[PDB]
Image (cartoon, rainbow, N blue to C red):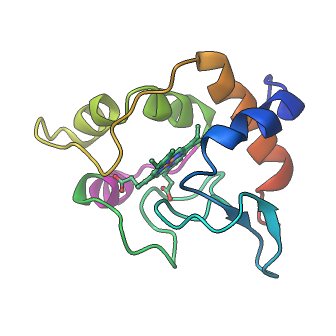
Amino acid sequence: QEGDPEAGAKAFNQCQTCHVIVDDSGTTIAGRNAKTGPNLYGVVGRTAGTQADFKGYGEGMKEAGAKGLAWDEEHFVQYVQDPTKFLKEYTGDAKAKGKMTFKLKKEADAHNIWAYLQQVAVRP
Ligand code: HEC
């Protein structure tokens, strides 16, 4: 919401190596065909670790979603900044790591990509 969606659309290039945003009709809104990560379409407000077509979720992600994690900005930003650190605290498991552990470099990108998802990845 307070980030720059247009700056986020551009910062999304960092994520398209592994994600894609493809609406229910099947149109690619961002990215080409990366499957490593889950389709980010409809992630806003979605319960962590529940994208129907994804099969590579780590246990930490499936459990955080089971403990009640649905994506909002606050969380989404903490997560991409340090994904392990976030899964350990949310999950309470000091042994959770996740399938992606790189830490985002800028916090602004995080807010901007969120403002962009809020503009293109919200499942009506
Ligand atoms: C590949 C090297 C990745 C890059 C680059 C990015 N993401 Fe990612 N993401 C990846 C994986 C394998 C997973 C699964 C994590 C696991 O432990 O299971 C994810 C997950 C996410 C999620 C969770 C979505 C869900 O369905 O609950 C989000 C919110 C997410 N990724 C965001 C994201 C953003 C914004 C990126 C660019 C800055 C990005 N990812 C890059 C793998 C990879």
Give the vertical position of 104 relative to 20 (above or below): above
Residue drawn where x is 28% and y is 59% of the image: 58
Residue drawn where x is 24% and y is 43% of the image: 91
Tell me residue 75's x, y (percent). Answer: 50, 34
Query: In which image quadrant can residue 7 be found?
Result: top right
Tell me residue 98's x, y (percent). Answer: 28, 48
Tell me residue 72's x, y (percent). Answer: 60, 40
Toward the viewer: 106 or 48?
106
**Does residue 85 appear left or right of residue 113 in this picture?**
left
Residue drawn where x is 58% and y is 51% of the image: 17
Q: Main secondary structure of the magenta part?
A: helix
Q: Which quadrant holds the N terminus?
A: top right
- Is residue 120 rendered magenta in the image? no
Toward the viewer: 111 or 19?
19
Tell me residue 36's x, y (percent). Answer: 46, 62
Give the residues in magenta.
61-71
Residue drawn where x is 58% and y is 17% of the image: 106
